Length: 50
Length: 157
Image (tube, rainbow over the protein chains, first blue to last red):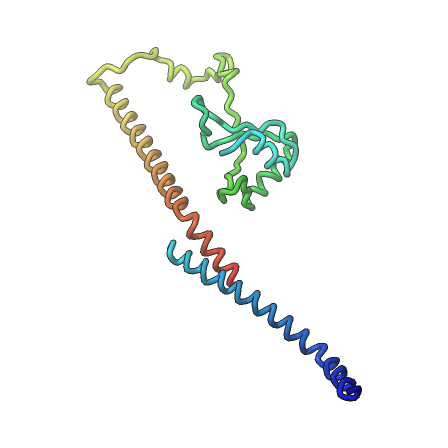
């Protein structure tokens, strides 16, 4: 049990940077998609006005 | 929609404003003009050149105000007789006293010519005013279109 775990802790230490990068990328993607949604909405409104 | 304090504070950036009153007619609606007087000539010149080269805007309505030097029309002194030159052409222009033009005479015909020229001048001025008014009305109808297009381009950028 102790060895299996010593290994589990060592593995979970390795993903320090990878999970952080994934989380930052995901939050950036969510912000990008919401901004693109705003883009399409206001663009079609402007097209209708034109 | 303007106020005296609006012009007092807006032009307070260039310098101290002694008076800033919107030119208003009898009914109370704004006449579209206004008078602003500074304290120092260099401050007035700086404000004039900054407004000419820049776009000085007052309110949310994105229409800047045109700024030019103030001509001073005086009605106190008028013109006294002794300050006239009283030279030879004054006697030439004072051969006969003011009167009505006799119909069928040379004076009446030349006055007809002058009146026609003056009426044509008034018609041309009215045509220019109409052209300016229609251009401004057309420019005003597109508030939302231009603003929305600029929003589109800025935010896509």
